[PDB]
Amino acid sequence: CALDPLSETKCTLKSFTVEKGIYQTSNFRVQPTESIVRFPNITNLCPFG
Amino acid sequence: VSMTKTSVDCTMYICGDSTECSNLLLQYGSFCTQLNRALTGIAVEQDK
Ligand SMILES: *[C@@H]1O[C@H](CO)[C@@H](O)[C@H](O)[C@H]1NC(C)=O
Image (cartoon, rainbow over the protein chains, first blue to last red):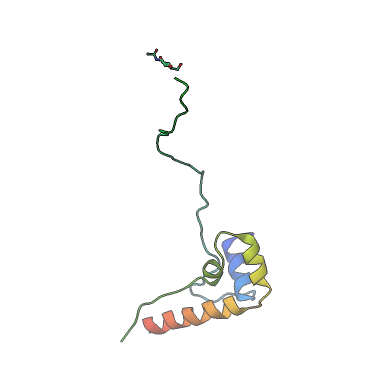
């Protein structure tokens, strides 16, 4: 199934001779590259100074 | 003459990025397959 797009089409159609047309096999998804966390400047500093 | 040529992905709708939800849904059978088939038929029907 995962060898090539035609093979995925064959698996989806459950056949060995796919006819001329357009077939939807899978869904494309973009996995997030990284995670970023942002917070405002902290003002509740301990009175060390 | 025609309505919005829409299509819905069953797996992504039912379950988000979580995989365990996908595995658990996989045991419900071919609900999602026939569900997508119905919408694809509707879309081709709109074009027709
Ligand atoms: C007050 O203490 C802080 C923390 O040690 C220091 O950075 C700061 O320079 C001090 N204030 C003055 C006027 O030196």
